[PDB]
Length: 136
RNA sequence: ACAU
DNA sequence: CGATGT
Ligand SMILES: [K+]
Ligand SMILES: [K+]
Ligand SMILES: [K+]
Ligand SMILES: [Mg+2]
Ligand SMILES: [Mg+2]
Image (cartoon, rainbow, N blue to C red):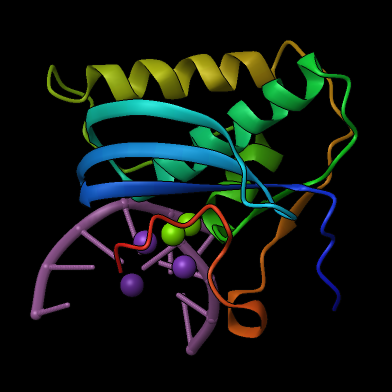
């Protein structure tokens, strides 16, 4: 329908999938970058999209903000709703860091509360989410 | 199929 | 063209 401009938008960026994963959150209205995660050497697109939403939840909660979060990831929105990131990525020494962060994000969700609406960014209608990395 |  | 996901 209408974009809710008073919101936080998040997105993953990667070099390969699986590959190097990062994410960022921006003010939907202004494009101001509000947070950026240091690149993680191996992860998946969906793991990064999940981490980005959870980081957004933590960021808004710390600031007493009731703004919604936009994500373009059907998968990550569902994983956050379920409090469970159902990634297929093998757990081995190479993937230990991303899996540690995902495990810690799930743990945060299981021990905290939030009312933040997590909304699907409608890329087909509105173009690329404002947190997009411009790499595609 | 749809969403990345 | 390849991959991650419901
Ligand atoms: K997109
Ligand atoms: K991109
Ligand atoms: K597929
Ligand atoms: Mg995305
Ligand atoms: Mg993007």
